[PDB]
Amino acid sequence: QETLNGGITDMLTELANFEKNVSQAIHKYNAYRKAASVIAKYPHKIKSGAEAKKLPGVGTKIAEKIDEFLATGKLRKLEKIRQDDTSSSINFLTRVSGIGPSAARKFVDEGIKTLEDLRKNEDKLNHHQRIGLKYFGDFEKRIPREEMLQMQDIVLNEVKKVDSEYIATVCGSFRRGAESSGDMDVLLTHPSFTSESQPKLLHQVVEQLQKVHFITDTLSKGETKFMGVCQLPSKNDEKEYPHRRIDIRLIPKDQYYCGVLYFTGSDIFNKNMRAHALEKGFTINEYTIRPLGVTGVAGEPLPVDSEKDIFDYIQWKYREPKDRSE
DNA sequence: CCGACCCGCATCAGC
DNA sequence: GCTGATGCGA
DNA sequence: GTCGG
Ligand code: NA
Ligand code: NA
Ligand code: NA
Image 1 (cartoon, helix red, strand yellow):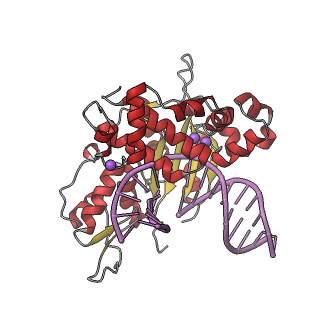
Image 2 (cartoon, rainbow, N blue to C red):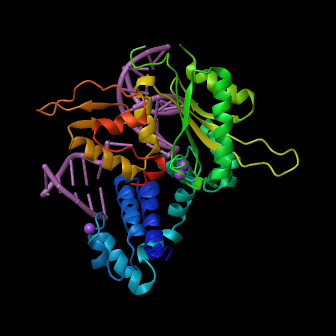
Image 3 (spheres, rainbow, N blue to C red):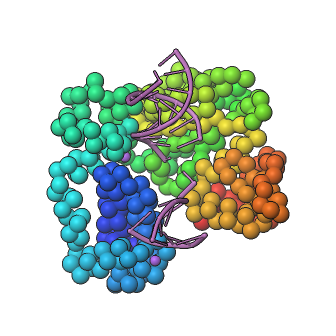
């Protein structure tokens, strides 16, 4: 029920997960999600599939499943997937970070189906999957904004202790003011790092955060992207905080604010802004805004030294992150 | 009728 | 050893 | 799965 249509939204999200994890049909997965997002925003209790079909992203098949769900309170197809041992095991194992549909299938094919089975077969797991297994429960917890604020202060301070010239921004829905987050997404830059130009810039920051024991584990790390695990320090007497997922991305200074814009979102806000930028003769991606010639040929990137600059180019009043829900 | 639907890093396949 | 494909994660 | 060239 939720905000009028949670049963339908829950059903669509479950169908999405089966498409992604078991059938390996990622476009169907995203079709079901989009339909769930549209419906979640529809401010009426839907009464028929035909009503739902009017909404963009709902077609004949989702309408039919909505009719069945309304008439009966259930979907047959979803009921049989639920009791299928292979589908439910594949679905479950993909909850481990680093285990996607392919690894989940091979594990289930070899009788590895549960966390206990994984705990028993560690040598069959790569490094990422072992870390995802170790923190299985913590990684499914949301992060309250209160903790994200603290996490933000540590990153910004540690970054400044390495080099005062680093610029670091915590983006994601947290930057839009969200009351919880699923992970922490940090965008980093330094004036010595441009698209046309000093080494170890990402490494130095990751190392600092490891030294003070904020970053506890590494999932992947190269010269421009780090994915890992972090944890707030304990009060010495209170319960330990859960381990959290954190990504850090090093971006060229001249592309920084286009990245900050992109990764702050929302996704709906980004599609809308790109769509408006096109109808003004501009193309914006996660790195640049460039003017379009009369035949549609993208010209050279325009200078960008703030988020505002981007809004100025396309004749749009600046909108605070708080106001970028769409 | 039928193709679109948006890359960094770890690891495998193959050479 | 290397190059390119694949899986994965957001 | 849904949309649209
Ligand atoms: Na529709
Ligand atoms: Na997974
Ligand atoms: Na998953």
